[PDB]
Amino acid sequence: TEFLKPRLVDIEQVSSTHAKVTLEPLERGFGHTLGNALRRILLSSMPGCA
Amino acid sequence: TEFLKPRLVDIEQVSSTHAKVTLEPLERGFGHTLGNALRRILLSSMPGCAVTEVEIDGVLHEYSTKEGVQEDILEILLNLKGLAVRVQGKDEVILTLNKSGIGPVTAADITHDGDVEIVKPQHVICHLTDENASISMRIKVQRGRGYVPASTRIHSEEDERPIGRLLVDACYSPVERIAYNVEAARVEQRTDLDKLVIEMETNGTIDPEEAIRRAATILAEQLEAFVDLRFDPILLRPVDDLELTVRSANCLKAEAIHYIGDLVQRTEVELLKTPNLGKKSLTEIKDVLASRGLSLGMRLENWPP
Amino acid sequence: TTESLRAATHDVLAGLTAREAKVLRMRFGIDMNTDYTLEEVGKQFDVTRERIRQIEAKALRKLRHPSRSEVLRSFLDD
Amino acid sequence: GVLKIVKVYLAVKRRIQPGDKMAGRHGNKGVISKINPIEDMPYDENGTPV
Amino acid sequence: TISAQVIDTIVEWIDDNLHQPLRIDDIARHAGYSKWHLQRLFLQYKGESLGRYIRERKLLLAARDLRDTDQRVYDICLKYGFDSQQTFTRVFTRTFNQPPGAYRKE
Amino acid sequence: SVITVGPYLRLHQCGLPKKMALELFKPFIYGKLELRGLATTIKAAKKMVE
């Protein structure tokens, strides 16, 4: 068990409302799963006032 | 707003090695994503030990035949490909095969061990038609995850193994069939919420609870990245404790010199001319100064400790 | 390979002494048409043939030094 | 004019890799585009992934 | 301890030095010793002149290179200190009373 | 070489296997090896590439 550990590198801030975040490569099937989890958390159960 | 919900109680082992585990608590909008993530990590992040390296006596290569064997070497290897072994104590074990007589030689003939467990004894391996000759082999079972092809393992091995050691493709995926279904659970107050029936078919390799725990551990380890991640001491030694010759430490402390700074401030070719030291001390002076990034007549940055 | 080898030999001869490189070029024939023998190099430079032999041997012994042969050891197979 | 001839007959596995032409009986000729893991493949409801 | 450990350095200098000859001016410099640093040693510990001891050391060192089956006989004496072939020939003739080839064949 | 079915890149970029430059870019490999000096000679650089 020697899975690779990610490391944040680029957090590029183009504007106050946009961001390009580069997360280091991991084993296959992990990046897409993490992206799906992130988008689901942010667009399905994101707490906020309206 | 907040919720913990201690859950995941499961003893379902009905009629086979196929568990029906319900996953909870699940919030509205997380079912499909949670199920897909769990399936991904249970199919990718589950290590398993199996047949990796075998050697059969009296066999030159895997493209030959053996007297008294009904099948071929390739068929025996393909049959051993679907064999799982449970190892608890160590990670690398060596099993032996010793079976004589006429009949189907199965996995039950392999010499068992205290920590080595066989999944099924009826796993057909080969067949012997004559009792004159027998079959014997040594299987080296190592622990690993993912999948290692033969073309990479043949290059990663730096030492050349002797003739007769066969190369076996080692599959490290114990989970093959798996699915998840999202249904509505019976809740006392918030009738909005639901259960996730997760079905899997493992060859008795990893327990469902242990598999879920390892999957959650791997997920937490790969998630914590977003949570957590946003002078030379031998130079200050005196002339006596510098591990030099005897005459290089006794004569220097007699001319008002007791530190390396007073020695490096003065010129070497002008100070070594005193009839108290020797010409060989220039070698030690060079080994002390030029080997640590020092020049002639330089000034030290911070000489006091 | 031959071009790199001859360039390296020319650089080594230029880095060494003048008369040593001249004798080595007149004996073996580096950047020279005719390959003179011992007596020819002698009659050209110095009548004493033993001095030419000593110069050639000293040049060979200096070329066999490890600090200067570390770059020529790579051409051992060629 | 030949003294000896030594034939080796070297056997190679040559496993499946992207770049091989595959077809069927009706004639659906093509090529192996990529080898994606079993996780990144579509699947049925119960037991048969694609 | 004689002249602050010159014996422990002379052997090291002899073992590590090249075929450069050893004389008063050569050796005394970075040897840590004066002419008198070495005269007392050569008189007490050795009791032999330098020209004979150095020649004997060179002969004992070349006794193995002659058995190493080397074809460049002219370079054997040069790689060990003898700057000329005639000097090494005379030294060997006065020491062993045998021709160079007679001992090289053995 | 054989074709492959997958973008895997942008418009003005294409995907090539390690070998193509394994056999075609070796002169440039030797040149930039002699440039930085990571190899002793060209004859040794050829063996290091092999």
Image (cartoon, coloured by chain):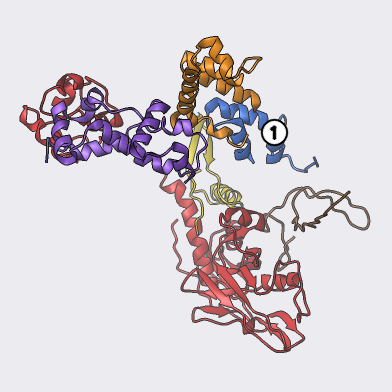
Q: What element carries label 1?
A: loop
Q: What residue type is labelled 1?
A: Arg
**Residue nearest the viewer, comparing B20 with F24:** F24
Q: Position of residue F50 (x, y in %)?
A: 64, 41
Chain drawn brown in the picture: D
Residue at image position (53%, 27%) is F36
Give the residue pinned by disc 1. F10
The colour chain F appears in is: blue
The colour chain A appears in is: yellow
User: Residue farthest to the front?
Assistant: E97
Task: Name the image quarter holding residue D25.
Answer: bottom right
Chain drawn red in the picture: B
Above or below residue C70? Residue B127 is below
**Residue nearest the viewer, comparing C4 with E54:** E54
The colour chain E appears in is: purple
Residue F24 visible in the shown view: yes
